[PDB]
Image: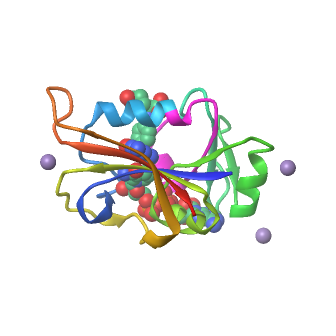
Amino acid sequence: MISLIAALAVDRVIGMENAMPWNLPADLAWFKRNTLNKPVIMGRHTWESIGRPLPGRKNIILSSQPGTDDRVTWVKSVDEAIAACGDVPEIMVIGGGRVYEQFLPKAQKLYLTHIDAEVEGDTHFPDYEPDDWESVFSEFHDADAQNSHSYCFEILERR
Ligand SMILES: NC(=O)c1ccc[n+]([C@@H]2O[C@H](COP(=O)([O-])OP(=O)(O)OC[C@H]3O[C@@H](n4cnc5c(N)ncnc54)[C@H](OP(=O)(O)O)[C@@H]3O)[C@@H](O)[C@H]2O)c1
Ligand SMILES: Nc1nc(=O)c2nc(CNc3ccc(C(=O)N[C@@H](CCC(=O)O)C(=O)O)cc3)cnc2[nH]1
Ligand SMILES: [Mn+2]
Ligand SMILES: [Mn+2]
Ligand SMILES: [Mn+2]
């Protein structure tokens, strides 16, 4: 099974200048819980944005060019990325925009955080046909002293 996980600001913005400008510790905690002990697939730009391997996960980087770091696994195509994950129940695709576009047709589940914040950005989550997806979990949180915007965690499953 392939799942995507992402955090979206208003208008589906996911990034600006190869960075995420907000800070939401509760969402990073949700990301860690839902990805730990699973393989994670990311594009090369997102690998550079993160800047170091994510512990407790098999890190698979999609890039057309040779890899430059043996702490992670480098693959050159979508099919190779999937094969490199082996026979696991759930593969987590962690972006960015171009990578989400390629894996969305193959995905059965979306883990989305909707952040109530307006962000100038240059990268967006793909348009996804709402009729194809059923909401199976949602949980709203107001802003607090640690998390400066309200946010909604949602899990969607393909119908
Ligand atoms: N809010 C969120 O949830 C979230 C999550 C992830 C990322 N982001 C943000 O998203 C932005 C990065 O997204 P992005 O669209 O610019 O880049 P991306 O999807 O991270 O990376 C694209 C790169 O991945 C490689 N690639 C992708 N598909 C490939 C394929 N089929 N075969 C071989 N290589 C492939 C290429 O690398 P080469 O040029 O090396 O071939 C391509 O240039 C940043 O702002 C980041 O902070 C946000
Ligand atoms: N829901 C969600 N939120 C995000 O912010 C997010 N970000 C990315 C891409 N960017 C990043 C940047 C940093 C880390 C990271 O360092 N994660 C640590 C969390 C510990 C911490 O710094 O709080 C990890 O161990 O997973 C992960 C993804 C991909 N999917 C996402 N998905
Ligand atoms: Mn091929
Ligand atoms: Mn197999
Ligand atoms: Mn806000």
Measuring from the top left, give residue 9's x and y in whole percent. 27, 55
Question: In which image quadrant can residue 76 be found?
Answer: bottom right
Residue at the spot 26% in from the left edge and 66% down from the top edge = 11
Measuring from the top left, give residue 25's x and y in whole percent. 30, 31
Residue at the spot 15% in from the left edge and 30% down from the top edge = 144
Measuring from the top left, give residue 115's x and y in whole percent. 26, 49
* Along the line of sight, the residue nearer the viewer: 97 or 63: 97
* Along the line of sight, the residue nearer the viewer: 31 or 140: 140
Residue at the spot 57% in from the left edge and 30% down from the top edge = 36
Measuring from the top left, give residue 151's x and y in whole percent. 26, 44
Q: Quadrant of the C terminus?
A: bottom right
Residue 51 within the segment the image draws in magenta: yes
Residue at the spot 46% in from the left edge and 73% down from the top edge = 129
User: How many numbered tags mark residues here?
Assistant: 0
What segment is highlighted magenta in the picture?
A: 34-52
Image vertical order of residue 87 relative to residue 9, above or below? above
Give the left or right position of residue 139, taking residue 132 as reference: left
Question: How has the structure been colored for display?
Answer: rainbow
Q: Visible in this render: residue 77?
A: no
* Along the line of sight, the residue nearer the viewer: 155 or 52: 155
